Length: 245
Image: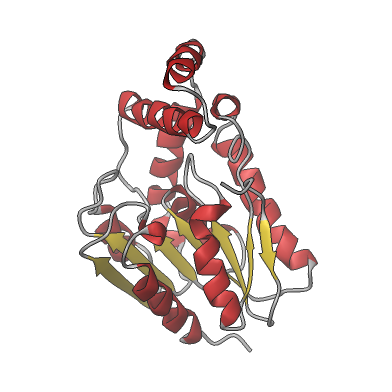
């Protein structure tokens, strides 16, 4: 477990912004970045506030702060002189990718298993606890110590869950503003979201250029699953299909 840090793989002129999922971090898009970098693409991956640190901090942040991190990520590349910027995000990152799509100039959009349907706050929170549990286990903490820490954790309500539902709904509601070439990626039997969200995106954006690929043997965190290699190739071919300079 290497300490979660933002990464910047500088290479050619073509830049790609990589956004991770809720509860995840830059490691979830690190292998994708390294691959693109090996193909001459400059990549940058920020870490959302409350992420890449002990679970407790997560409750103190929502989409508002994460959106600020996303925009700072875009700005991070713009300030570096990079003019053409494509964006690729995982799950929540895919929602922020689409939003960026109609907020600033984007060369291309890759959404990987982005939700367009909302889950109950109870469900979302279950995922949060399961995330904290696993993070505690990865800390080398004894089982007993884990169960104690997890008790104090539930002691702090998470207001963020509701803002997340709203973010999802708002973006879906603005899909018709997206014109940038879009590549929709979806795990056919995604265990965390309704895979149909892939159809929502593809069918509702206004992009004259768009494609959708279904991965039959993958789970939600598709970047870390067994079809990763093909996924890398498919994204590369899409980026290569864009104009750039």
